[PDB]
Amino acid sequence: VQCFSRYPDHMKQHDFFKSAMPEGYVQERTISFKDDGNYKTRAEVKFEGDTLVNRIELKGIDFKEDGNILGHKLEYNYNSHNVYITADKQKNGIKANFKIRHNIEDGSVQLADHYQQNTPIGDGPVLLPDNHYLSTQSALSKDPNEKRDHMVLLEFVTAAGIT
Amino acid sequence: KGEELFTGVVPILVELDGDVNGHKFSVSGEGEGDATYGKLTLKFICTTGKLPVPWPTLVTTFX
């Protein structure tokens, strides 16, 4: 839900995400885990009344049974990263590339390469940006009163790269 | 319209249907976002039982 990223005033004409609203956008990703499998996602992000909805379909293939993913060898935390955005004027949307480094319990790291593509659902005009990035900072926690498998996420996202 | 719909606190809903190596699962997420501060506060619950993949692997898909 990158439509909640803080775009500085001098960079507001580069906010594709918010300009596609209320009709929204389709977000597609290929997440490739190094020496393991891949996730292929298709999501629809749009407004349903005053509520922002993110409907996703995830498909994961070629994963190792006792790899870092299916064997649950990753620590419960998240590192800071940058999402590098570029325009896709041919598809009236954007493309994004970034690397996520998950911490493994032995002290090593599991690389997850992300390729992203976003296209508007509506016919209305959108903002096609110049090259920039989104500085992300996340923190994961647990609700002590919850017994179901869960995750509490606190995230801060700010756009940068253009002065 | 557009940016004007994000000037304040907006409620968020996340619904995911997954299939990883045959292991089918569903996650429901609720929370809010304040774009003025680029802040996201969300809680995700696996509605099909236990998640067959670690939670950190899904953060970018969620969000």
Image: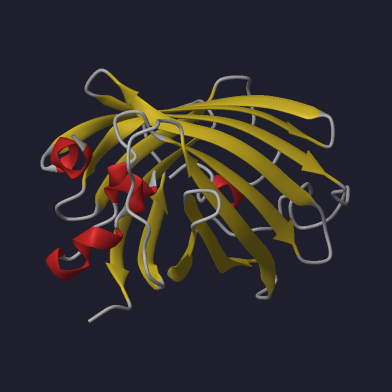
Give the quadrant of the C terminus of chain A. bottom left
> Which residue is depicted at the point 71% across and 46% down?
A39
The image quadrant that residue A11 belongs to is: bottom left
Number of marks in the rendered image: 0
Outermost residue on the bottom side: it is A163
Q: Position of residue A72 (x, y in %)?
A: 71, 50
Q: Position of residue A26 (x, y in %)?
A: 51, 37
Left or right position of A133 against B11: right
Is the residue A62 above or below the residue A111 in the image? above
Is the residue A100 above or below the residue B35 in the image? below
Viewer-proximal residue among A140 and A137 = A137
The image quadrant that residue A137 belongs to is: bottom left
> Which residue is depicted at the point 43% across and 33% down?
A45
Viewer-proximal residue among A15 and B58 = A15
Viewer-proximal residue among A149 and B59 = B59
The image quadrant that residue A73 belongs to is: bottom right
Q: Is residue B42 visible?
A: yes
Is the residue A148 above or below the residue A133 in the image? above
Q: Position of residue A2 (x, y in %)?
A: 37, 49
